[PDB]
Structure formats: C-alpha cells, structure tokens
Amino acid sequence: SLKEKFAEYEAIGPRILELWQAARNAFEAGDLARVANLLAELKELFKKDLNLANAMAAEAAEAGNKEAVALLAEQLERLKKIQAMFAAAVNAFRAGDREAFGALLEAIINEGKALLPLVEAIKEAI
Image (cartoon, rainbow, N blue to C red):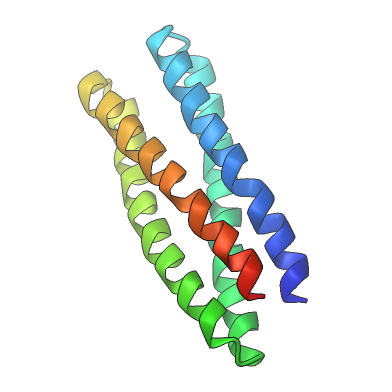
C-alpha cells in the first residue's frame, strides 16, 4: 500500500538529518574515517529515500490521489537538489577542500531540515 511506504519514508528523513549532522561533527573533530563511514551510510539511506518518494508518487498516481502526487513532486525536486549537493560534498571530501565541504554540509543540513515539514503534509493527503 501507499501507507506502508509512507511509514518507511517518514522514518528515514530524520535519520538522514542526524547523520549529516554527525558527519559535520566528525569532520570538525578530524575523524575522517568516521566522516567516510557516515557518508557511506548516507548514500544508502539517500538512495532509499529517493526510491520511496518515486514509488509513492507512482502509487499515489494509480489511486488518483492528485494532492499527494503534488506534495511528492515538490519533495522530489528538493531531493534532486540534495543529490547534487551530496555529490559535490563527496568530491570536496576526497579533494580535502575543507571550506567547500563545510559549506556544503550546511546547505545540505538546511535542505534536510526543510524537507521534514512537507513530509507531515503527505501523511495527511494519503
């Protein structure tokens, strides 16, 4: 069902946010091995998040829930931007561009925060 997916989707956003913030803390501490570990887990969770948003858009389309498709579309537009920020963050990490990495971390975390309120609305539309 569409509700079965939303339940997984809703749980994963706050986990992602927490790991982005842990990545930042570990980076300021110099714990680069843990930064890497956190990034490795973030790529998995982010892939999971994006796949669920698309699947729910497909599922909400089948049911004619036009309101949910629309909420899911603006969330997918944000996800696409986060994906590009993520890719730039990973390259900054590998290059040791500390100022780029630190700035990208801020931008990603703020985008992560901005996603959560809209996830709430999706609960209501399904």
